[PDB]
Image (tube, helix red, strand yellow):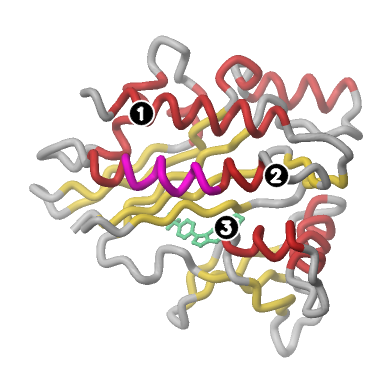
Amino acid sequence: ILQHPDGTVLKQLQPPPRGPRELEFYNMVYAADCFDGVLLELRKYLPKYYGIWSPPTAPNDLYLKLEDVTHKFNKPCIMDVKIGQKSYDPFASSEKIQQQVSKYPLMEEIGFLVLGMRVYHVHSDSYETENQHYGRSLTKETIKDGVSRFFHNGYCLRKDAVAASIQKIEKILQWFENQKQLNFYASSLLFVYEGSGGEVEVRMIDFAHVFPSNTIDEGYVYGLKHLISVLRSILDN
Ligand SMILES: FC(F)(F)c1ccc(-c2onc3ccc(-c4nnn[nH]4)cc23)cc1
């Protein structure tokens, strides 16, 4: 992800088939002639899409130009959470399924995985960051405290941002409870709150494994529900 001062990010297409799949997802949802009620509502929860972009002198080099969801913040606190019980898709080989489950074997049980976070600490005017090994090290016993960390600014727990996050997720959940045409594997929620403010973003990202479906995305729903439950518990801290 390249942050551009114009308030967008450039995301390089991942190798095939993942990159091409994510391109077609954005093209389907943001089709200018789309009047599918499900897809028009879905746009509310995604980064705005500005189309495919490539460097003037390098048409081979494909990017997605997306809204930078962090742009309007002064000191954005950012957390990426992968949602679902399965981070492998319906076309995964036994090898790939094993590869994916082993990356985080607790995915089925918890329904979400923290990919990383960047948290502003007020007292030091500095950031603390966690990488993929943080979330992959969390268990049922430690997930509540693991998520809580995102919302602690060194001084206090930001229950305002926690409650706001629940309210934003509930709208995404409602979208999922009212559609049976897409299932999302290995996709994420991007959480942003103001570290230096009640303003909160929660947006769906990373669509390299979104597939047409005839059923509720039950894995995604389980994950959202569990994540909401954890956030709800944190409000009692
Ligand atoms: F923490 C960082 F590194 F500073 C960071 C991470 C993600 C973003 C970010 O802001 N808007 C996005 C929109 C989409 C994505 C994205 N899509 N797929 N993978 N990441 C990422 C986005 C911005 C900053």
- The image shows residue 203 at horizontal and vertical percentages of 52, 54
- The image shows residue 53 at horizontal and vertical percentages of 71, 79
Q: Identity of the amino acid at label 2?
A: Asn
Q: Distance between the residues labelled 2 and 3?
A: 14 Å
The one nearer the camera, 214 or 110, is: 214
Mark 1, residue position:
232
Q: How far apart are marks 3 and 1 (CA)?
A: 21 Å
Magenta residues? 163-171
- The image shows residue 69 at horizontal and vertical percentages of 46, 64
- Quarter holding the N terminus is bottom right
Taking the image as shown, residue 84 lies to the left or right of residue 6, namely right
- Quarter holding the C terminus is top left
**Does the Cβ of the disc 3 residue fall within 8 Å of ligand 1?**
no
Question: Which mark identifies residue 178?
Answer: 2
Q: Is residue 167 magenta?
A: yes
Taking the image as shown, residue 226 lies to the left or right of residue 182, namely left
